[PDB]
Each structure stands twice: as structure tokens, then as C-alpha cells.
Image 1 (tube, each protein chain N blue to C red):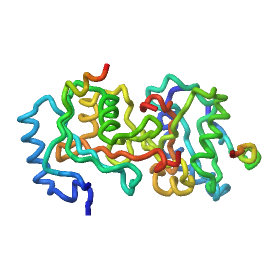
Image 2: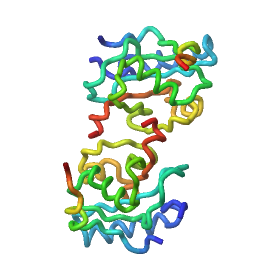
Image 3: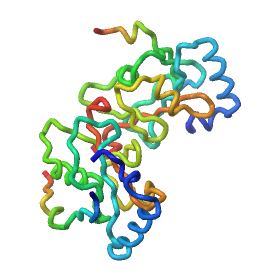
Image 4: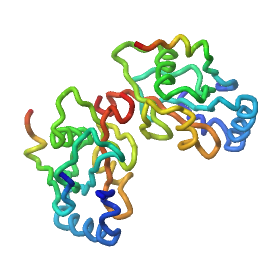
Length: 119
Length: 119
Length: 20
Length: 19
């Protein structure tokens, strides 16, 4: 450990949590954001669970993660859905949530450095 | 153009095509390369089906597609596997084929502008 | 360093709105 | 129409330089 969030929290706990936040924060998309597997070059975030305003596009989430990570302009990074799915930056996060959310109700995302993918 | 290879060819025919070509070309990967779904920025390739030496890397293949397309410096793209999966460019295609090949035996790739994903 | 699994990182509107 | 494969040749590969 640390392991993936899915392995640190039972499915039952994750399902329950999602039901509750959606209840308390109906306009927020619940997002798990973790480092891509074996990624060591980019830093870990202070928090794993994000509450993302549902009217926003992917690009707004990317700009936020970029700022959470404190990357300088020269560092490029990927924000992938699930294991390695590329998501258009003009795509609404509510749409990605609908198509790609887990059975437990979270949307899972991972980030990786350009070096991880050979750039 | 703009009809997926899978809609232009029956499952039975695609399986047979892959099986027959792999007999004659055991060190070649059968790769379908198409424009990203909803992609309008990059030009189309003349041909969709490629036979790629398996020892080659994903990066070398990118350089080949850049040449087929005759692209300008400013036009950049990623080569994604299946619908939208990002793969390290440093990976041998033999490795990608083993992991990502389709049920019919083809490896499906789509090319998309990097800017679509915020690069 | 290891991330807190207990608290949500709430992305605010104000955060979205800046810098602009 | 994709009747025939587009074969990436070794010759095409040795045309791909590296810095």
C-alpha cells in the first residue's frame, strides 16, 4: 500500500458514499483521481476524492488538476478515465460521468506524465 | 471514407483475413488505422489496413503515419488503441498486439489531434 | 504524502472562474 | 477500399531517422 482506492474501500462503502454525496451535493460529480499505475514522476495529491461541478467540461478539470499538481508550463500530463481512456477536452464532465462511471457510482481517473507514455 | 472498417466487413471475413495473412506474414501485425471518431482536424489516409513489422515501436509507426498524411509541424496527433486507449509510444507493437488485439484478430488504432486532448 | 481518502476535494465555482 | 494490405517496408523504416 497505498493500493488503488477501490482496494482500500469496500464496494459497499463506496456505493453508500456515492449515494450520500449525490444527496448532499446534487450538482457535483464524484471523481476518484489517482496516479496512473507505477507513475512516480508526478506527485500524489493531498486528496483522492473530488467533487466536480457538473456543468463544467473536461478541460476545466484538467486545468484544476494541473494546478493541484503544481506543474510548470513545460510539464505536460495525461488525465485518463479508468485505466487509460482518452477524453476530449471539449466533452462535458456530466457526459463522461454517464458513459464511464463505475458500478459503485464513482468516476475513476488517473494521471500520468508524458514520460510514462514515451514523450 | 468515414465508414468504419468493422461496418464495411463481416466478422467472419475479418477473422479469416487475419488468419490467412498471419500464416504468410508471421512477424507482421495486422493493424486497422482510422480517423478518431468525430475527428475533423486531421486528413484521411488513403488506406486503412496496414501490415506492420512486429519488432517496431508505436513511435516508429506514428512517424510513418505522419509521412503518409504529409502533415505540417503544427498538426500533432496521438495514436490510440481501440476506441480511445492511450498507449506508451515506447512500446513494441508486438506487445500492444498481444494485450489489445480485437476478437477478430485485428489491432484497431485511431489517430486524433493532440489538441483535442488539451495538448 | 499519501492521499486522504476521507475528505472530498470540492472544486468551487470561484476556483473555476479565476483567473480570467 | 482496403482490398490489399498497406505493407510497411523495411525500406520505409530506414527512411525514418532519429536525432
